[PDB]
Amino acid sequence: SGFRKMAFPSGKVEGCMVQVTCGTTTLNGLWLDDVVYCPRHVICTSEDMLNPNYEDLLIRKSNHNFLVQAGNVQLRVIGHSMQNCVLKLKVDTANPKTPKYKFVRIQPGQTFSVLACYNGSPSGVYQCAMRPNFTIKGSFLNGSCGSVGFNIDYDCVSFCYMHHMELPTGVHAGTDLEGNFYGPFVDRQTAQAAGTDTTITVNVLAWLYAAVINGDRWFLNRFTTTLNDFNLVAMKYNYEPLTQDHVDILGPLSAQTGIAVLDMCASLKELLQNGMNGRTILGSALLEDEFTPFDVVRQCSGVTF
Ligand SMILES: NS(=O)(=O)c1cccc2c1C(=O)C(Nc1ccccc1N1CCNCC1)=CC2=O
Image 1 (cartoon, rainbow, N blue to C red):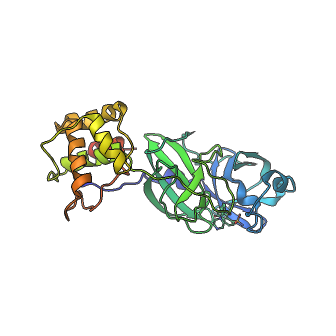
Image 2: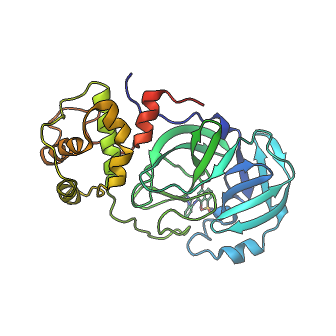
Image 3: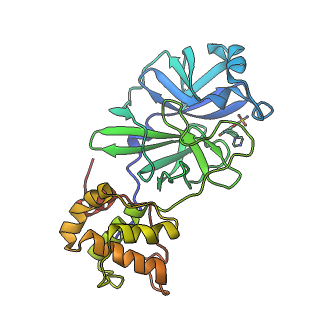
């Protein structure tokens, strides 16, 4: 037992991390089949990042300007094209370590593992969540772009995230693997504001179910509440409004646990109105919202790859 913020095994993704160099800009790229995906700002200097015209800047670039290396073995770029805010570099050889993969655009609240790399080689891995305002609180130094976020289900690596920039607030933004930014962000070095962030209510409830599973039961209350009443309380504390879909996705936890979902929301209302009172839940003094119900069921089922 015990509960931990657990990342996916990163090997299958380590096997596709290449270094992409263009002029003097160097960052990370993802080598799948005979295509290397990378952020389009690889074609920019920092003097270009204030207001870049990516079409005009890419037009004076040719295939021989891009240098792709996997560790030390090298890739011959034989084509290139810009899709939204990513560059697709067609190379001479196909990645022998290409796993079964998909490109999917995740929805807010859902989680993924980030493999943080620099110069095409991995440095760390950690689990994070796509905030309701389409940001993530990762850790990304300079050179870290092009690092990817992914989920792994049995055989399949579903890539969902490519890191692009750090907001002046200190949080991070990126695109899906088709180059479309999550949220209202542009790959431009200017002031960009994320919206009001809110807490992923269903995730907090899944984490409380995990807590009940692992022995911590002090927050377990005796009230229940209406869905509308809990939503009244949740909107005051800047929580996302709970829908019947959320209650349905919490069904397995509510059944293994024996605690009806609405009573768990009653306990959560009590925690929001009275605080945690100096105690902890699963080693945390705050209400954790970066576990989806599926993450809890994974850690309790020992789902493997
Ligand atoms: N010559 S470069 O094109 O600025 C550059 C050079 C090396 C590595 C990176 C960058 C990037 O931009 C970049 N993404 C980005 C996107 C929009 C606005 C600013 C940035 N960055 C943030 C990190 N500091 C440099 C500016 C990621 C990198 O890993």
